[PDB]
Amino acid sequence: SGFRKMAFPSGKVEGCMVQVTCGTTTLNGLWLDDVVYCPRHVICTSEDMLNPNYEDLLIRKSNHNFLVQAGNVQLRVIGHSMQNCVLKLKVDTANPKTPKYKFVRIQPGQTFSVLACYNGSPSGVYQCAMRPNFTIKGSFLNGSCGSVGFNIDYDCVSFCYMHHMELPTGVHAGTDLEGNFYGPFVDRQTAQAAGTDTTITVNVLAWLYAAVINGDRWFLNRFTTTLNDFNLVAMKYNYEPLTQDHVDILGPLSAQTGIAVLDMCASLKELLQNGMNGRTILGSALLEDEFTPFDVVRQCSGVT
Amino acid sequence: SGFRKMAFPSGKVEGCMVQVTCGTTTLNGLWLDDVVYCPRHVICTSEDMLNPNYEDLLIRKSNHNFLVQAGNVQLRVIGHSMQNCVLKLKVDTANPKTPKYKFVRIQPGQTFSVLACYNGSPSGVYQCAMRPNFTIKGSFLNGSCGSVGFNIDYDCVSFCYMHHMELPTGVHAGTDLEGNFYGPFVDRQTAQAAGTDTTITVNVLAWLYAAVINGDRWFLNRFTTTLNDFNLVAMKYNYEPLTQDHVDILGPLSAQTGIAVLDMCASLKELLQNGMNGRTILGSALLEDEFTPFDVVRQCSGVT
Ligand SMILES: *CCC(=O)N(c1ccc(C(C)(C)C)cc1)[C@@H](C(=O)NCCOC)c1cccnc1
Ligand SMILES: *CCC(=O)N(c1ccc(C(C)(C)C)cc1)[C@@H](C(=O)NCCOC)c1cccnc1
């Protein structure tokens, strides 16, 4: 029993982190096979940041201008290319610790683990979710760019995020491993305001199921609701709309606990309307939304 | 910017996890050098649990009765001994992935990372704190015993916890790596109720400093207090007493933010007395106490 904000074991990803330097800028890179992926803004100086023309800045760079260090050893760069907002540095050595991997582009509401790195060295691991406004609320300092987000399915690492920047509001923006930003963000030091950070309803419901499985049942009410009635309340509270796809995804949790999804929706509706009244659920005084229904099943079943 | 409940990168510890089986019981073991450490209750059956005599049960076990598997390969057990509540199984092969390590016994309030494992395989990593009542609030299912808690200082892993059991209230109890339980708990299926789970005051103050560093400043008040006045309020709210040692430990955070420790105490006193009023601090609606002052400095400075 017990339910924690749990990250995937980070070992497989630690074996991929390298340091990438270009001129005076140092950030992290991800070394998979004979390619090192890193944010293309590694080529920018203190001036460039404001309005960079990456293709033009890249013309002034050769393979020998990208310094890649794996541990305390230098890798030889034999090619470089820009794919969207990432640079791909071809090195002469395949990473011997390359795990089985995939590049995936996640949808808002999906969670992942982040291995925060500095100078190609891991500092910590935490669990994030892609917010509905395509930002992530991470813990990233100067030099953390190139740190990656990932999920693991047995022995295959699916990389979903690469850190690029912090918006003026302290939230984070990044790309998938093909260099495409999540959301409308651009790798430029300009006014970029995030949209509404709504609550991921399906994740809150999954976490309420986790609470019931773990013995926290005080919030269970005597009511039910419909998807349309629940959604009117959800809109009022800046919660994402709940769809039949979300109800279907919550089916296994509904089956395990014997609580119909719409009954849990009615309990969540009363929690939104009445508040917590100073009570807690799974040690939290707010409704947690960074656990997907898959995360709840995985943690409650002990998937390794 | 941003502040997350961050665990240490788990790779170094993943390379130490093995599966230990004795009879019909399988749990996790920690393989360091040529020794595998695991809970001694691996020798117990469905009957034994109630009132086990470990020395007597151990007489019926030989080296060949302990099956140790590292990955998909079997390790040869050439000796076994009981040290307090842990078994030490001497194997004929030193773990090639043994990191630099220490065994440390932590004090209440200290945090650590847990690599939850099943069948010798890592499932996830999360950050815990040793509660003032010597329990931990983990996420552990059947088969998680032998999962370990640790801190990392650059390349040295200090192991501080080994999971042994869950109390009837769903909280967890375990030992240090010398097999001594934290708190008064015993490895027996009997009535063991935990004491008061008070809040770790020095950790809450550290986290309020983290909030100020990260821009969450609404709770900063125009007051100050004394250690004795603050402590009268702390006792009333089931918070641990604050000592001059804690004030000294918070010195670097006080210096960085320019907020005297006693001023932050007065802000915490008003938060206890007035509540949050529906507001949040670092995305939390309650006062977080599982970040030590060292954790706040480490995360806010990017220690790798
Ligand atoms: C990794 C580099 C870095 O720390 N940061 C950064 C990111 C992007 C850029 C360009 C403008 C695209 C060239 C420069 C520097 C910062 C960062 O985002 N700085 C701007 C802050 O906006 C409010 C960084 C700092 C903290 C966390 N992540 C990144
Ligand atoms: C690892 C074995 C296991 O899952 N558990 C366990 C621990 C200790 C014992 C002895 C009684 C000491 C022989 C048997 C089995 C359980 C556990 O603690 N069971 C009792 C539950 O008490 C409420 C376990 C279950 C979940 C999390 N950790 C351990």
Image (cartoon, coloured by chain):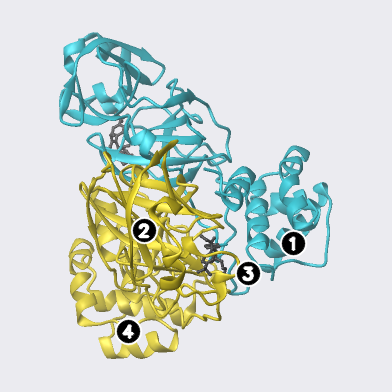
Chain colours: A yellow, B cyan
> Residue drawn at (63%, 69%), measured in percent from left and top?
B276
Above or below, A260 against A257 in this view is below
Callout 4: chain: A
* Mark 4 lies on residue: A241
Look at the numbered disc 2 and say if its residue's Cβ is closer than 8 Å to ligand 1: no
Residue A119 image point, x, y percent: 50, 47
> What's the CA distance linking mark 4 and mark 3?
28 Å
| Of labels 4 and 3, the one closer to you | 4
* Mark 1 lies on residue: B267
Quadrant containing ligand 1 reads bottom right
| Of labels 2 and 3, the one closer to you | 2
Rendered image: mark on residue B276: 3
* Mark 2 lies on residue: A149
- The amino acid type, in three-letter code, at marker 2 is Gly
Instruction: Work out whether residue A261 or residue A84 is closer to the camera in this orientation and state it.
Output: A84
| Of labels 4 and 2, the one closer to you | 2
